[PDB]
Length: 46
Image 1 (tube, rainbow, N blue to C red):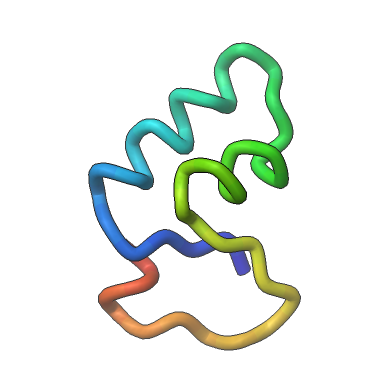
Image 2: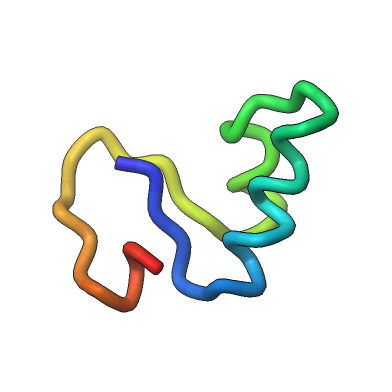
């Protein structure tokens, strides 16, 4: 489950994808989260 608590974070997170960066790296800096489970609510799945 790849989640993020804000559109602002989500945006630059996906922007970090385009240079060929692993979400793992981007999430950890951006603020987004990559969790094995945990069905994120509508404020973390944004």
